[PDB]
Image (cartoon, rainbow, N blue to C red; front, side):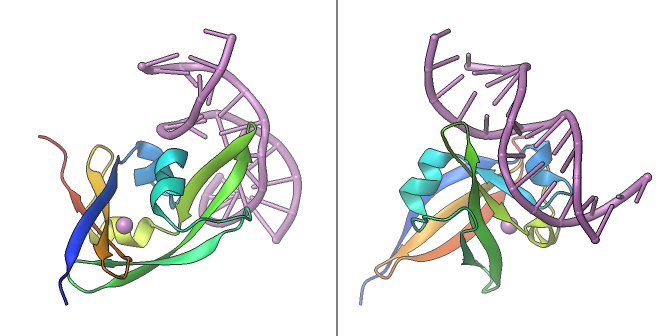
Length: 111
DNA sequence: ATTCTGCATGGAT
DNA sequence: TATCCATGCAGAA
Ligand SMILES: [Hg+2]
């Protein structure tokens, strides 16, 4: 059958996202809009392939923030290093239709 | 000291 | 006023 890659959204890494803590923050709008919906704080494990085949597995989860939710992927440090990534570079998420498989990529900062 | 948690804050807009 | 995510910041180990 016929296949296509739908871009979902991107995230320009912050220091907090890029450093040692291992959590990459997702803006709520984007999280709820493009990832599986989730009803509990401690969310689900989420598998994302990269261009060169490799599956990564993060916990996709959130906490109560104000009267809403703040969202994150936990356990990302391996992947960031593997991709030689820093604050200011950018990660792009993307979906493959039909079937809705999640994949990812990144690019270096503008300089 | 250190890393991990689980939020809460407040700066930026 | 409001929103909200980058970073603070305390337990707990
Ligand atoms: Hg990654």
